[PDB]
Every structure is written in structure tokens, then in C-alpha cells.
């Protein structure tokens, strides 16, 4: 998963 | 109190319409174990936030291990070093964790304010650069 | 919260006009250590209450050891068996102590209601005894 | 000391  | 987010069961309850269920690695139980709350928006329907360091992650894949993702993206989060269950914490330990959470929420707001300001400063700097050309 | 009474320093603060100071065995520090809060009235200016079992004691003498008095008058009070300092309690332990305090406050109100009723029942019984004589 |  990845940052806002 | 709203020390509720320290309770895993409260955290699990936030994933009411989390889409990744049995069969997946990032299930609500695993996400809640890792410290995440489900904070869905429209642009990001799988948006999840650590209740403790406030790191926000999206774009989850089925094979993602929530603990590993939390470690990769926010390696200094003290929640990751809590080895006891909540009820086994001492009050002193709990209070210290709660102070550290508050320090974390100031690093987060500060960070969002910096980002917003810099977005503006770039645009402004660009404009004045054009004027300075003559 | 008003979990304040579990803090010794809060308890010591209640003895603002407690009369027994340095030189005495039942000093505010010792009274607070034993679990007492100062609850003065007019008929009883040295009235003190255990925050945890709610036993109320008055008529203190200089040589009274508050722990010993608490044990003598309320030998089953769980607070007397707390050997740790507050901050060293686990949350589970703290919560269990707080449930036990609540059970204690129901035994106290129940007890005061019983006493009040019996005072009345005696008077009533006395009156009807006279009528039954013929 | 003594009870209320
Ligand atoms: Zn975190
Ligand atoms: Zn007591």
C-alpha cells in the first residue's frame, strides 16, 4: 500500500 | 473515554465497508491489529490511518501485510513497539503512550500545514520569477 | 477523569483544614496513604472517608495509625491489598479495582437505606405494640 | 478512631  | 482507538475491537469496527475480507492478507482484523482505522473518502475508498502516528495509506493490494506496510511507511511509530496487550499496559506506560500520540498529532498537522504552504509558495515563486525576467 | 481519588496527592489536598499536623501519627500524608479523604461536617469536623470502601471514621486521636484504623474498621477493603503504586497498576487491574469500588458504593447506599428504614420500623413497631396491648 |  501507498501514502495519501 | 476516546481512548477507544487503543482498543483493537473499536478499530476493527471502523472497517464496516472495507472491501478486503476473508482470503486476503489485509483483512480488517489484521489491519486493526496493525493499528489502522478505516477512513474512507471518495477519491480513496480504501484509505486507512494509524490511530497512533496518523500515517495515511491507500492503494492496498490483497497480499499486503498491514504490519509490514506500517513498518515500511512509518518505521518510527511507537505503536509498533508495543508488545503487550492493552489491558497489560501499566497506567504510567499508557499515559506515556498517550502523550506520544499527542506529539504525533502535532507532527502531523505541522506536516500538513508545511505541505500546503509549499504548494502555494511554489506557485507564487513561479509568478515572481516571470516578473523578475523584466 | 474523577479517577482523581485514586491519586494520593488529590487525597492529601482534601485535608485543607484537617487539624492534625506534624507531630501526630494521623497526619494528612498518612491519612491519604491509607485511602482517606477529609469530609468535614459540623457535628464531626475530623470526619474522614475511605475513597474506596466508603467507611467513615471520626473521633481521631493523635496516636491513631490510619492504616491500622482502616484495617480494624474495614478489614475487607481491597485498597488495603494494593501493594503497587497507582502508575504501576495495569489497566486490567485498575478497571477491576474501579468495578470493586462501584460494588462498594452500592453496599454503602444499601447499608444507609437499611439503617434508615430500621430506625423508622422500630418507632412504628413500638407504636403498634402499644395498640396491640388492647 | 470510631465509626459515624
Ligand atoms: Zn503508526
Ligand atoms: Zn477502605
Image (cartoon, coloured by chain):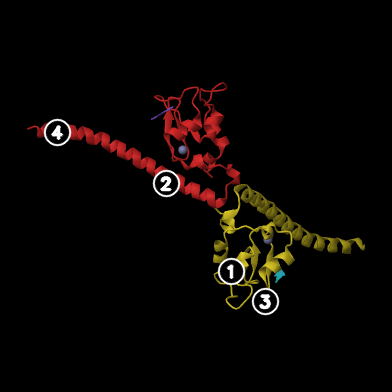
Chain colours: A purple, B red, C yellow, D cyan
Q: Residues within 10 Å of mark 3 (few under 14, many from 20)?
A: few
Front disc: 3 or 4: 4
Q: Which residue is mark 3?
A: C63
Q: Residue at x 47, y 23 (%)?
A: B61
Q: Which residue is mark 2?
A: B103
- Cα separation between marks 3 and 2: 49 Å
Letter of the chain that mark 1 sits on in the rendering: C
Do the CB atoms of the residues marked 2 and 1 lie less than 8 Å apart? no
Front one among B51 and C107: B51
Front one among C55 and B90: B90
Q: Which residue is mark 1?
A: C29
Dot 4 falls on a residue whose secondary structure is helix
Q: Do marks 3 and 4 share a subunit?
A: no
Residue C40 shows up from this direction: no
The image quarter containing residue B1 is: top right
Which residue sits furthest left? B134
Q: Which residue is mark 4?
A: B129
Amino acid at each position: 500500500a501507498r501514502t495519501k | 473515554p476516546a481512548w477507544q482507538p487503543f482498543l483493537k475491537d473499536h478499530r476493527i469496527s471502523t472497517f464496516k465497508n472495507w472491501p478486503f475480507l476473508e482470503g486476503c492478507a489485509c483483512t480488517p482484523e489484521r489491519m486493526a491489529e496493525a493499528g489502522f482505522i478505516h477512513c474512507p473518502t471518495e477519491n480513496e475508498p480504501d484509505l486507512a490511518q494509524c490511530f497512533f502516528c496518523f500515517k495515511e495509506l491507500e492503494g492496498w493490494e490483497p497480499d499486503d501485510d498491514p504490519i509490514e506496510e506500517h513498518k515500511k511507511h512509518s518505521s518510527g511509530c511507537a505503536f509498533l513497539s508495543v508488545k503487550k496487550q492493552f489491558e497489560e499496559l501499566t497506567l504510567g506506560e499508557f499515559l506515556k503512550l498517550d502523550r506520544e500520540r499527542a506529539k504525533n498529532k502535532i507532527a502531523k498537522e505541522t506536516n500538513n500545514k508545511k505541505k500546503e504552504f509549499e504548494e502555494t509558495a511554489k506557485k507564487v515563486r513561479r509568478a515572481i520569477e516571470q516578473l523578475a525576467a523584466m
